[PDB]
Length: 256
Length: 256
Ligand SMILES: CCCCCCCCC[C@@H](O)CC(=O)O
Ligand SMILES: CCCCCCCCC[C@@H](O)CC(=O)O
Ligand SMILES: [O-][O-]
Ligand SMILES: [O-][O-]
Ligand SMILES: [Fe+3]
Ligand SMILES: [Fe+3]
Image (cartoon, rainbow over all chains, first blue to last red; front, side, top):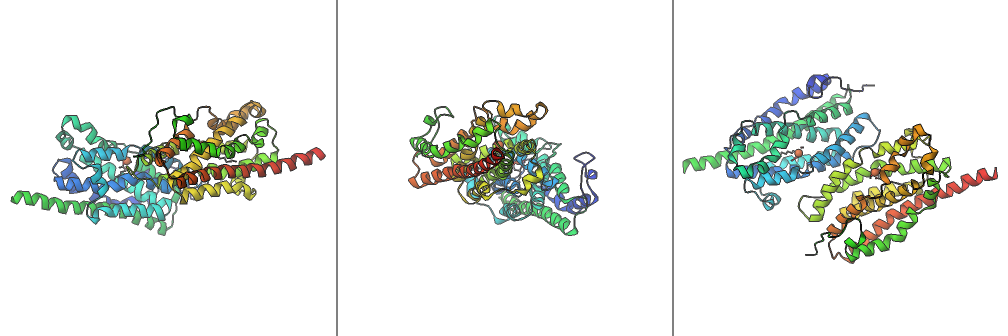
């Protein structure tokens, strides 16, 4: 019947089939270059220029603002009792849409701590490299199967985001640099996403595996791999463009 | 600025503008003939034929199964901070999608207590009069503005459903007719919807009023009125067809 049911711990690759473990391996370099990106090492250390911090916060906003909408669009593809993976997806999406309730508000507060206003967020004056991620996310959510779109969003983006947010928070410098009275409100978005035991991406993976089963086609596996790597690669494109702006901003002041 | 902010209690028509009070009045007969329908008086009294009870449970299923999907489709139309009514709608829909988590399961349990299996539900062998409501709900959710689709679903259908479910539960006969060991599980869907102080439709109305403001166009008001009455009128069409089947079923046995 090719039916998957997890036996081992949620948050261990070994609890999933060989093909899923292969998928993780095949996407690992694409993931690594995002979650260990120089931009995040610099942000961790409070080094980023005002220009780049502003571009980061504005550029990230559409994905943040629309994240529960990707989930909604995926929920719209599901039907009750059509497949055990589909029931799992339905329930999870209905629970996790609520989880995001205040997250866009937190991003607005984070932004305001760097002088980025709601008007700035809404204006979206940033380079096109920074918007590609949002366009991909809407396209997959709109047009692809649930399994692929969930892989692109709740697995790839949320998983990477747990890790980069943890890296930003990892040594206390960034947080301690905010004045005490501003810090809790400024840091809230980061703190909500940086939490060592984030079951969310593993829960997403479990849904994907249940949908796909023990023996998915090579074609389906390639579709998943390409969607996951596309999400990472658009995060990488965003980060590379920000670092080009960083090097210019910092060099200008060094030479002045 | 035409901005609406409620001062009075949530669940009183007088807390809303004159146009909203007019809207309620204009839709009142359409509503009444559903919420006081003979079919529900009979169901209350455990009188309905097996044939009709089965048709009711199968026919209602698509709307039940898809209800959180209508909400999802409406959430997809919203954007952060574009309008105060839209922020209200976004937050409410994100909270209330979760509320429906188990409701389709409860309907399956209610159905099974009348010998209607999941297979029966999925097969959807009922007259077309019974499916019209589901087609309307998807069409408005897919194609209409948020305000109109919310009016059609969370206001009209959920409001009427609070009232008809309360009527079915109102004298204890229907519930007491189930064997004790089966009763809690059979009655759960009804009980969850029959609760005297159901703020859900009033919350929906508040969102609609906030979206529309103090002085909506006559055209927008007519769109709301026609959408709300269409939802009621499709419930009425469903109920009228069921009662035609009831009269035939009962008459056949009376004459036998
Ligand atoms: C370079 C990446 C910038 C985009 C990050 C988007 C993270 C989305 C996280 C998701 O949980 C929604 C949210 O809470 O903001
Ligand atoms: C004649 C009406 C039959 C359709 C009733 C649909 C009621 C939908 C209620 C909504 O809360 C979803 C649910 O919980 O089943
Ligand atoms: O996603 O938090
Ligand atoms: O809707 O409960
Ligand atoms: Fe989030
Ligand atoms: Fe419900």
